[PDB]
Amino acid sequence: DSDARLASDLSLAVMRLSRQLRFRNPSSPVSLSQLSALTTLANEGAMTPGALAIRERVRPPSMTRVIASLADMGFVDRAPHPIDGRQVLVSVSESGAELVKAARRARQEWLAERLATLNRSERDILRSAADLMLALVDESP
Amino acid sequence: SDARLASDLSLAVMRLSRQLRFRNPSSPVSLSQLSALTTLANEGAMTPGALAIRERVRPPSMTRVIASLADMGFVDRAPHPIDGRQVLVSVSESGAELVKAARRARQEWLAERLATLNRSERDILRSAADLMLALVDESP
């Protein structure tokens, strides 16, 4: 009963809050999808376009265009794959890596401002909540 | 330490929303198209210009999203951003149903995960859900 309502409310809250945090790309010529691909590439390291498409759950034609756009802006490099495949490996450039870190700082600074409008008790609840939510994604199959 | 609360909470919400996103049923819409559709369904009819502002995408990108959604029959029309500037776009019945279907999939998966926690932990998440909505000024 209130089980259903907690799943509804918590899902809503995390989607709505994350929506705002995704919007914390400092203005920049990269889209939401481009930044997401870049972030994955930066955090997980060099990979092929096919693997990246899979990691993002986007189909290869769409991801190949994202990659091309990121490369054009110099945010991702391309190198031939060692071991003749013959695939390409894509990785973040230093401007790409810096962009991902800049975006993360931006989310953090934005969030801190919002959290400051709450009292200490509320922030304490969100601390426990943050730990639990992190555990939930860790523990998911 | 409130510094680390901004860091951890952001990380948690980015990762969890990522998992919930992945539970959206397979569909012919991209993430950006779904977002526009969802906004349109939950907040109501708007002009293409208003939808673009709401989605924080540049008007040319939004015109193609709107056009694509009309093509798929998920919105009633796709007015030209100049010639139709003052025309309202709304979700169709199939579009609204897509949005509701996605919403159910996310919450049902989440309910399964929440069931692995104890009552005290769920109490915390219950309070946190309200607080997080308040953070984005989206309280009732």
Image (cartoon, coloured by chain):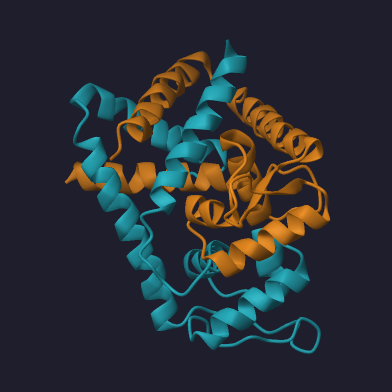
Chain colours: A orange, B cyan
Residue drawn at point x = 61 percent, y = 25 percent? A117
> Is A26 rendered above or below residue B89?
above
Most extreme residue toward the top is B1
Quarter of the image for residue B46 reads bottom right
In the image as oriented, which residue stretches furthest toward the left?
A1
Foreground residue among B14 and A54:
A54
Query: Could you say where residue A35 lies in the image, as x and y percent from the top left?
Result: 67, 48
Q: How many marks?
A: 0
Taking the image as shown, residue B80 lies to the left or right of residue B89, namely: right
Q: Given the current orientation, which residue lies at the most extreme front position?
A: A84
| Residue B29 position (above or below residue A125) | below
Side of B74 where A67 appears, left or right: right
* Residue that appears at 31% across and 58% down: B105
Location of the N terminus of chain B (image quadrant): top right
Q: Is residue A23 visible?
A: no
- Of residues A46 and B133, the one nearer the viewer is A46
* Residue in the picture at 79% in, 35% down: A94
Residue B137 or residue A56, whichever sits in front? A56
Q: Percent from the top left, x then y, of residue B73?
A: 48, 86
Quadrant for residue B100, please give it: bottom left
Left or right: B110 as drawn, with respect to B80: left
Query: In this orientation, does residue B65 appear?
Result: yes
Image: A105 above or below A2: above
Across and down, in percent, residue B4 comes to 57, 16
Q: Position of residue A20 (x, y in %)?
A: 61, 45
